Image: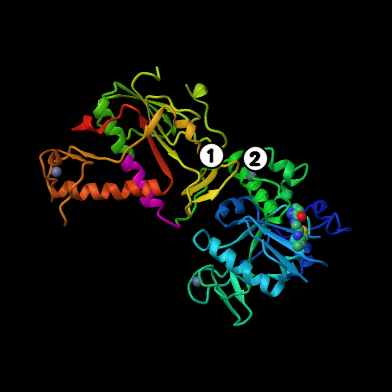
């Protein structure tokens, strides 16, 4: 945890707060913010913030004493008076709780406000924030993130309906990391997808994007592990199953003499009984721009497997699994320059999906293939895509009907999680019969 006696640089704040001391600790800062047990500091370290990336909410307040525009990286702008029209703080804070609860309940057990701090945002916290000792929800065992003055009760993000204060938020000022120049000039160095439209929400979006760029694009820590909040395990199991299925059938159908497996340096053979000559080539997850095939690269013999090795243009003799950054899920967070921050056990920033990368390939059709014995150890199954000896013979046996439906469920899970599959144009399932 971050010592409250650590120094906070105040130069960023001196425009909204003329005369602010240069010599400043977090202790004195919190006191100036109007605030006074498991919550040692409202501010956290970059390391703590990285561990709670899912909780990150970029936050900016803009002035014109007169009204204030509060912007958040969700896209919401609220106007408080002492896009939405001006309203007093006692109704504004109700909206802040509802918005953070709906955004974060399926993501994290807290909120981390990510700031490019110039003053108003920090002096505005006293109007919708309360702090105190760590607590638990009144209705469950999750830690409390909201408080209600109507009933003097605490709630987590799931049980906060009607609550009016944010309780024990965390926060981090990006301007402490040692930057030169304003927010827009540092953000626009790495990103063109987020504009500067002179609304507070635009600043909040840029601030979070810059943070993510610094902590996951330029710097990368794959040792950090993140809790399970979803179907992580079923998704990862489904990916290994689809990988085995698709490569096995591609070898059986086209009988490539060699396979170039390009990507993770710890990859293992996904079809260990295949006759082919299996050759590995090491590349780590690219976090910034897609690899250039010319730098990566007889790759024109046999087939190339690119299983989450994002390249700019796949060769024509490839099998490919590429993550689609546009997908909406609790695992996939907005990232930098169209990229997305996929957090499933580990945090993988991923360059933006680009359909031109697949120009030499086609989409891979669903199919189930099996050469296993028809032995069991219900509604009868009818499908043209169940490629088994039994379907060839007229009637799908029960074992293969069960496995087909399991494989379809895993296939559909992996697609819905954002993954997309692409194959060489000559792939043809008829060749497997
Ligand atoms: C209603 C009060 C109010 C205050 S400021 C504002 C509009 N926001 C900006 O001009 C701005 C500058 C940087 N980001 N946003 N509205
Ligand atoms: Zn609860
Ligand atoms: Zn950006
Ligand atoms: Zn069968």
Residue carrying label 2: 192
Which quarter of the rendered picture does the N terminus lie within? bottom right
Question: In the rendered image, which quarter is residue 118 located in?
Answer: bottom right
Question: In the rendered image, which quarter is residue 19 located in?
Answer: bottom right
Mark 2–mark 1 Cα distance, whole angstroms, equals 12 Å
Give the image's coloring scheme: rainbow
The residue drawn where x is 78% and y is 59% is: 119
Q: Nearer the viewer, residue 68 or 140?
A: 68
Q: Nearer the viewer, residue 169 or 409?
A: 409
The residue drawn where x is 48% and y is 51% is: 328
Residue carrying label 1: 352
Q: Main secondary structure of the magenta part?
A: helix
Horizontal and vertical percent for residue 254? 27, 25
Q: Is residue 1 above or below residue 276?
A: below
Question: Could you say whether the residue bearing mark 1 is in a helix, strand or loop?
Answer: loop
Horizontal and vertical percent for residue 417? 42, 49
Find the magenta span and give its range. Answer: 229-242
Judge whether residue 270 can be spotted in this image.
yes
Q: Is residue 426 above or below residue 210?
A: above
Looking at the image, residue 60 sits to the left or right of residue 159; the answer is right
Determine if the C-beta at disc 2 is less than 8 A from ligand 3.
Answer: yes
Looking at the image, residue 11 sits to the left or right of residue 397; the answer is right
């Amino acid at each position: 945890h971050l010592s409250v006696d650590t120094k906070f640089k105040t130069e960023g704040l001196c425009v909204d707060i003329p005369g602010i001391p240069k010599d400043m600790t977090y202790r004195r800062l919190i006191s100036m913010m109007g605030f006074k047990n498991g919550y040692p500091n409202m501010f956290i370290t970059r390391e703590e913030a990285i561990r709670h990336v899912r909780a990150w909410i970029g936050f900016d307040v803009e002035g014109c004493n007169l009204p204030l525009q509060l912007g958040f990286s969700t896209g919401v702008n609220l106007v408080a008076v002492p896009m939405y029209k001006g309203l007093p703080w006692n109704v504004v804070r109700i909206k802040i709780v509802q918005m953070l609860s709906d955004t974060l309940k399926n993501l994290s057990d807290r909120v981390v406000f990510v700031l490019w701090a110039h003053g108003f945002e920090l002096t505005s916290m006293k109007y919708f924030v309360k702090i105190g000792p760590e607590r638990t929800c009144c209705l469950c065992d999750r830690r409390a993130t909201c408080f209600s003055t109507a009933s003097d009760t605490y709630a987590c993000w799931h049980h906060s309906i009607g609550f009016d204060y944010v309780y024990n938020p965390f926060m981090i000022d990006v301007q402490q990391w040692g930057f030169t120049g304003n927010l827009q000039s540092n953000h626009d160095l790495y990103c063109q997808v987020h504009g500067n439209a002179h609304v507070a929400s635009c600043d909040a979006i840029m601030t979070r994007c810059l943070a993510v760029h610094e902590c996951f694009v330029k710097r990368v820590d794959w040792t950090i592990e993140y809790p399970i909040i979803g179907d992580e395990l079923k998704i990862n199991a489904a990916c290994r199953k689809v990988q085995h299925m698709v490569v096995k059938a591609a070898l059986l159908a086209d009988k490539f003499p060699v396979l170039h497996d390009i990507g993770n340096p710890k990859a293992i053979k996904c079809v260990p009984q295949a006759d082919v000559e299996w050759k590995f080539y090491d590349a780590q997850p690219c976090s910034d721009k897609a690899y250039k095939i010319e730098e990566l690269f007889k790759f024109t013999d046999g087939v190339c497997l690119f299983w989450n090795c994002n390249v700019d243009r796949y060769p024509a003799n490839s099998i490919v699994c590429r993550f689609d950054t546009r997908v909406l899920s609790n695992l996939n967070l907005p990232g930098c320059d169209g990229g997305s921050l996929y957090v499933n056990k580990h945090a993988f920033h991923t360059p933006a999906f680009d359909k031109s990368a697949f120009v030499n390939l086609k989409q891979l059709p669903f199919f189930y293939y099996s050469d296993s014995p028809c032995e069991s150890h219900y509604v009868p199954l009818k499908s043209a895509t169940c490629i088994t000896r039994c379907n060839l013979g007229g009637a799908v046996c029960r074992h293969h009907a069960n496995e087909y439906r399991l494989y379809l469920d895993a296939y559909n899970m992996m697609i819905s999680a954002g993954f997309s599959l692409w194959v060489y144009k000559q792939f043809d399932t008829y060749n497997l019969w």
